[PDB]
Length: 12
Length: 273
Length: 99
Image (cartoon, rainbow over all chains, first blue to last red; front, side, top):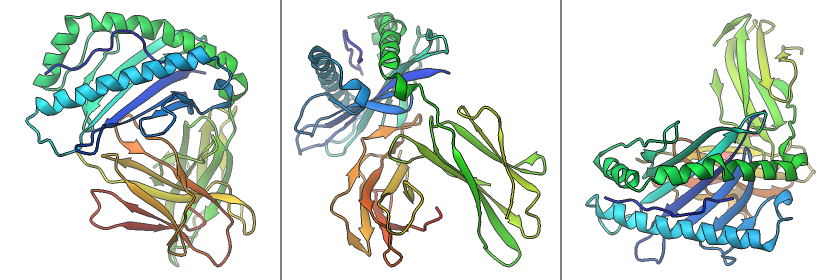
């Protein structure tokens, strides 16, 4: 089972 | 014995030839059980194990949705990272990710990890206490502030302490005849002839599972020798060998010691010609 | 940044002339991911090779596995040609039965 919920990106 | 379940994601960029490639595999401790590929024609989270095909259709629908949600974030990570490094628009740069969770012999949470890389260099990671990050430059530090002002770790701890272990226990219960087995290695020792007054003993260990073994030579009691990586046999087993160069005439004084989880008592190997 | 692969060519079961078997070519430890691997018989290519998926180790270095089905014979020679970015020329590894 994968990870569900509010995937965040990288800021730079 | 302990058990684990990990996930590996990859996103290689391609400029001018379309969209970045995206491969995502999933492992129980040493057995791949699912995969995905952005170039195959299925566009679905395809099974790769016998004990996993017996799940319903909603499971596969959810898995496909989530693995497609991950790639849409990798594709933007690539662009942002290329932009904030003053790099060209013609090379191919790689982003990798990995996470999972461990359980003990009593099948309760033991450890959890979540990492992130860029061009093969560590970028950011979740510490052993699952509450603080580990930066590596000014870039990682700014990302750490952004992720720490959105409690990202709090959201990513519930999963690894709850649902990861729940899924791992469900999988371990279903595929019991495959995941909970230990195969004892089959060992033999050979002989070469490099010159007139030398030799090269070798200690083989074939077709064992899991992939954690140790081979050591001992010149009558003292440790020392070229080893090779544990290589996959292709059908869910593994192989390994270790060799020690030795002057000729002294061959009944060397021993090879084999230690595997599937072996109750340590095995000793001596030259019996 | 860039690492160079490590090649091993072996057979699944212990080789024996006349019995069906498999030929593996396990490359590991390279970076980046774009690699070209071929299994050769008598110097010519083989058309029906399959490979596993792109995984990586704890230090972010990839590894693959190419395999095909063959029948060993005392007259034929098998090999594995690999070509990476960090290699200035291809690398031909032969299959000696004891490794």
